Amino acid sequence: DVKLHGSWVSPFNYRVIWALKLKGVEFEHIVEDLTNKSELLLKYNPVYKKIPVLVHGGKPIAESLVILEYIEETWPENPLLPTDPYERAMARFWIQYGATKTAAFGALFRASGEELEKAAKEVVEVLRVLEEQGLGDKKFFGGDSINLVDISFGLFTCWLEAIEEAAGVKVLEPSTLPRLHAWAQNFIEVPLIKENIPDYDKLLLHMKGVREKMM
Amino acid sequence: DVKLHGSWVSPFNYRVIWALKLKGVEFEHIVEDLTNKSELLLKYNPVYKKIPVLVHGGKPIAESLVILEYIEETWPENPLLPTDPYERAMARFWIQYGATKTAAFGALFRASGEELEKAAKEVVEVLRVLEEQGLGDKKFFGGDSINLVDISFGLFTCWLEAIEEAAGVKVLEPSTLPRLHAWAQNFIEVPLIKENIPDYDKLLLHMKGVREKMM
Ligand SMILES: O=C1C[C@@H](c2ccccc2)Oc2cc(O)cc(O)c21
Ligand SMILES: O=C1C[C@@H](c2ccccc2)Oc2cc(O)cc(O)c21
Ligand SMILES: [Cl-]
Ligand SMILES: [Cl-]
């Protein structure tokens, strides 16, 4: 009834895995080979031809942020967004902030030496705004438990750690981002997240390969 | 009770004007001078320092797409989104498609001659996907009346017309995009839209100035 056209490494696909597991939704995970995309993937997502694609009752939903809101509306129990409209707008605002800034992380796999340091410092500043104005003193972006905002920022945990190791630069450190670093540790320790993340060695190998083609 | 920090030309600000007027919400329009931003604008939107910013009960909401969903949730009567989750996901998908592609329209004010023709043809292709897969045979993206998707694409009416005149290229034409061109005419003729759009001569003068600094 629910199928997820995914990947073993995509952070965008893992957002969907987390939301489905938080709702207790049974699903079939179909891992796509991106060098030879299936006929179902091209039919279900003709506009972008990308994963993830959620298929529910044979009907496709593409784009991880659109999928997450669909899951929240379709399975409303175990809510992943607040009820108050102003609080929901703040959650959507921070999710969109992450979506707009995820591009500035590309410079980490494009720049070198005394240019890569500047790219890392710019990314620390992006994360500091999120820490100060978004997270604040809460344990999670969702308060006492994870919500769609935590899920949307999960890529700043093991995926960012792998990018840091592949590029040879430091970004999310406790000295510079104390609350965000504590959040990243708490997020990765949530049993649902810990049991549903790529193997770090495999993820690091994937990130090293991505950095190689981006130079 | 409701204030809108706006502009006389921003299409993003006009999205918010339309949604407020469709809900019958009374508001004060505060036109900001972007060369000397008010202390209230910098306090209400510290992350982007941009308009529009909706202020409701003294609490600010920035980013036109976030504001639109806040208005829809706060004033649920006269709905601007469908009730079915799959239909709501399709609406959010097309809104995000427009938000991702609005950047490719910048090339219209950057390129010249036999390069500007290629940029215009690329934009026609972006609009054709929206026409075929999004609009289809419906009068509006919202069916028989305008919804958040029509509002999000309203910039493809008089703002795109002004960009076409300023740049000297044609994009949205009836021969090439029959259904989307009929939609743009029907949208601009909706009394709520017709009574709430910038004066074309002033908008064209603004677009010519924007093209001059972008070259
Ligand atoms: O576009 C991105 C974003 C990037 C990232 C991860 C963590 C922090 C910042 C940026 O990770 C990726 C990995 C992929 O397998 C495919 C992607 O398309 C991306
Ligand atoms: O970013 C944009 C988008 C652009 C547009 C309009 C119509 C069709 C495509 C693109 O119009 C604008 C006008 C502004 O006063 C300020 C802006 O920041 C924009
Ligand atoms: Cl995605
Ligand atoms: Cl905006």
Image (spheres, coloured by chain):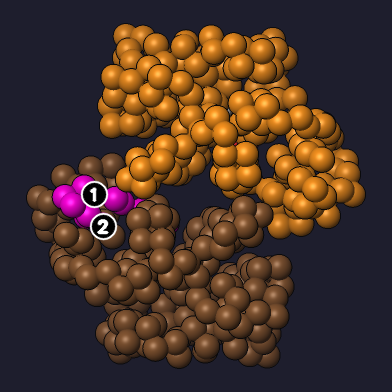
Chain colours: A brown, B orange
In the rendered image, the vertical position of residue B2 relative to residue A177, given as above or below: above
Nearer the observer, A128 or A52: A52
Residue plotted at (62% across, 57% down): A84
Residue at 53% over, 83% down:
A184
Front one among A142 and B164 = A142
> Residue B178: x percent and y percent?
32, 12
Question: The numbered mark 2 sits on a residue in which chain?
Answer: A
Q: CA distance from mark 2 to mark 1?
A: 6 Å
SS under mark 1: strand
Which chain contains the residue that carries disc 1? Answer: A
Q: Quadrant of residue A126?
A: bottom right
Q: Secondary structure at mark 2?
A: strand
* Quadrant in the rendering for residue A16: bottom left
Residue at position x 63%, y 90% in the image: A174
In the drawing, does residue A37 fall left or right of residue A142? Answer: left
Whether the residues at callouts 2 and 1 have beta carbons within 8 Å, the answer is: yes
Q: Which residues are magenta?
A: A54-65
Kind of residue at disc 1: Pro
Question: What's the residue at 22%, 54% (across, down)?
Answer: A56
Instruction: Residue A54: give its label.
Output: 2
Q: Which residue is mark 1?
A: A60
The image quarter containing residue B118 is top left
Q: Magenta segment: does it hold A59? A: yes
* Image height of A144 relative to A122, above or below: below
Amino acid type, label 2: Leu
Please report whichever mark, 2 or 1, sits nearer to the chain's N-terminal start: 2
